[PDB]
Image: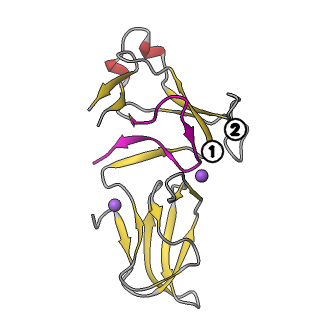
């Protein structure tokens, strides 16, 4: 619990460095950058506390917000790391076939078969969740001309249904972690 959240020990303001954040469909302010540092500072920039904050962490307070001592200001899953969409749209399953690239596992979930666990044809397959607009047009990742296709590494856990509406910052899949 403590290893996967930040609770500040004194009042101060949140200062985030190297951060990209977006609000998802659950009303969570989610960090989508991978080398973010969160600092508790005073009004003059003196550092009180400093923490690294992982990709996918949820913030209760954004950059520049004042917080009081004892307040929990970030939370992330201790045992998984997410794959998060950077764009809003609708989910489209790609190369996701039961028994060949994914298996059902149990609430139920789709689990991506790693390379060795796949049928002959499946080893050439690359399961992905593509984000499309309402019409089915490919959506591009912001900053690039690259499509918002998120491939799933083996053991990735997916709970989304195909075709479902999705918002930027929503988790596409979770990679099981120690
Ligand atoms: Na946590
Ligand atoms: Na969003």
Q: Which residue does the numbered mark 1 point to in the structure image?
A: 87
Residue 121 in the image: x percent, y percent? 44, 9
For label 2, the SS is loop
Quarter the N terminus occupies? bottom left
Which residue does the image show at 40% across and 36% down from the upper left? Answer: 159
Q: Residues within 10 Å of mark 1 (few under 14, many from 20)?
A: many
Q: Which mark is residue 140?
A: 2
Q: Report, in whole angstroms, how far the alpha carbon at label 1 lies from the one at label 2.
A: 8 Å
Q: Please report whichever mark, 1 or 2, sits nearer to the chain's N-terminal start.
A: 1
Which residue does the image show at 56% across and 44% down from the upper left? Answer: 85
- Drawn side of residue 73 relative to residue 144, left or right: left
| Frontmost residue, 100 versus 92 | 92
Region rendered in magenta:
158-178
Q: Is residue 81 magenta?
A: no
- Drawn side of residue 86 relative to residue 112, left or right: right
Do callouts 1 and 2 mark residues in contact (Cβ within 8 Å)? Answer: yes
For label 1, the SS is loop
Which residue does the image show at 67% across and 27% down from the upper left? Answer: 136
Residue 63 in the image: x percent, y percent? 57, 73
Query: Which corner quadrant of the image does residue 132 belong to?
Result: top right
Residue 38 against residue 136 in the figure, above or below? below
């Amino acid at each position: 619990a403590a290893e996967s959240s930040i609770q500040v020990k004194n009042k101060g303001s949140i200062k985030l460095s190297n951060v990209k954040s977006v609000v998802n469909s659950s009303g969570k302010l989610v960090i989508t950058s991978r080398n973010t540092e969160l600092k508790l500072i005073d009004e003059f920039g003196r550092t009180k506390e400093s923490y690294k904050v992982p990709y996918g962490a949820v913030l209760a307070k954004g950059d520049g917000e004042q917080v009081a001592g004892g307040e929990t200001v970030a939370n992330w899953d201790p045992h998984t790391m997410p794959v998060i969409t950077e764009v809003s749209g609708f989910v489209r399953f790609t190369d996701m076939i039961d028994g060949q690239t994914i298996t059902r596992q149990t609430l139920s979930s789709l689990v991506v078969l790693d390379s060795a666990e796949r049928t002959a044809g499946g080893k050439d397959l690359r399961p992905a969740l593509k984000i499309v607009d309402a019409q089915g047009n490919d959506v591009l990742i912001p900053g690039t001309d690259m499509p918002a296709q998120y491939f799933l590494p083996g053991k990735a856990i997916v709970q989304l249904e195909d075709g479902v509406q999705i918002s930027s910052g929503d988790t596409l899949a979770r990679i099981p972690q120690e």
